[PDB]
Image: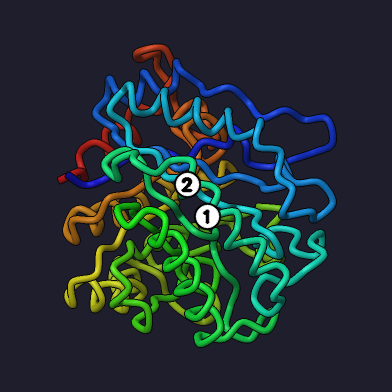
Amino acid sequence: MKKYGFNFQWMYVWEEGREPEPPDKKALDFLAETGFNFVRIPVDYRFWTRNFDYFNPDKKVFEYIDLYLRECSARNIHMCLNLHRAPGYCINRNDIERDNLWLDKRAQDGFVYQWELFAKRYKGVSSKFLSFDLVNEPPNIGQYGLTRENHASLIIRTVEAIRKIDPDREIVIDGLGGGNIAMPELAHLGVVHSGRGYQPMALTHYQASWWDGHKGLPEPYYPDLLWQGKVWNKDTLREYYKPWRDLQQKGVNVHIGEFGCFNKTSNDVAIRWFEDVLSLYKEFEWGYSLWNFKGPFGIVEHGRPGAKYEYYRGFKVDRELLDLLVENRV
């Protein structure tokens, strides 16, 4: 059974005094009632770590993760725990970190220790219900000193550390270059390779303040969107996914950990793009997880101009988008 669901930001970004959110049981009920069976939980290690003191985690905070797992499992939903901001790295505001995970031994030791903590805490929980997504969207080769070699070495070290404690724990790794680049060098590790559905960024992240490349972009149109001297359409998406498909043909399990469109793009344009990526996922037999359930990248009153919402099982949803998400499952 393929994994279809949503990412939830309950413990996504830490701020002084901010407590992680309780699981959104009503949202989880919606997922269960509409056939979704997957939830990705990207977390900020600062929720349990003070001033980079990696080896002194506040384990009391893990009770929230226990709760998320319990509520997901009760509704037959698989939970994928991800370190979004990990010791020494976050794709967003990496400058806030003291260390650099890709080169610093102290950060790597802290990172491995975090994963060993979770491996020990959840040893015995079936992979049917729980998987570990090591680190969200690693940077581009040449950024922060990352190379395919040192990234692979760190992933292998972490995977071996987790497996020494719990050999049955399913592990997921994100593609390089912000989840865009396939990793044939890690194909034999027996882990899920997780890609993304945000291309073309000119469409999905149009007017997204956190994305530097949004500067000077024209109002998105689709298909055949001209961006960076390249025309984007379904054929271009196939080219983009080819390296991932080549790996899947070799026996590697692939999944789309995050995908979606921001809420500044015209809805007709967004829907047209969704039809292409989702039809490709169906053809490839890939599972997928939308970035938001509620929010700009979600199905509940996202806000795109032209969109219409209707009450359905507890929420005001974009029925057209919800239908597309359901129709492309295999």
- Looking at the picture, tell me which residue is in the foreground, 257 or 86: 86
User: Which residue is drawn at the image coordinates 34% and 69% (left, top)?
Assistant: 237
Residue 229: percent from left, percent from top? 52, 82
Q: Amino acid at mark 2?
A: Lys
Q: Quadrant of residue 107?
A: bottom right
User: Which residue is drawn at the image coordinates 45% and 69% (left, top)?
Assistant: 175
Q: Is residue 327 above or below residue 146?
A: above
Q: Left or right: where does residue 284 sit relative to residue 306?
A: left
Q: Amino acid at mark 1?
A: Glu
Residue 96: percent from left, percent from top? 82, 59
Residue 221: percent from left, percent from top? 47, 57
Q: Is residue 82 above or below residue 106?
A: above
Q: Tag 2's secondary structure?
A: helix
Name the image quarter holding the N terminus: top left
Q: Are marks 2 and 1 in contact (CB under 8 Å)?
A: yes
Total numbered circles: 2
Residue 65: percent from left, percent from top? 53, 33
Q: Residues within 10 Å of mark 2 (few under 14, many from 20)?
A: few
- Looking at the picture, tell me which residue is in the foreground, 160 or 176: 160
**Residue 116 numbered tag:** 1
The residue where tag 2 is placed is: 120
User: Which residue is drawn at the image coordinates 15% and 46% (left, top)?
Assistant: 330
Q: Is residue 182 above or below residue 71?
A: below
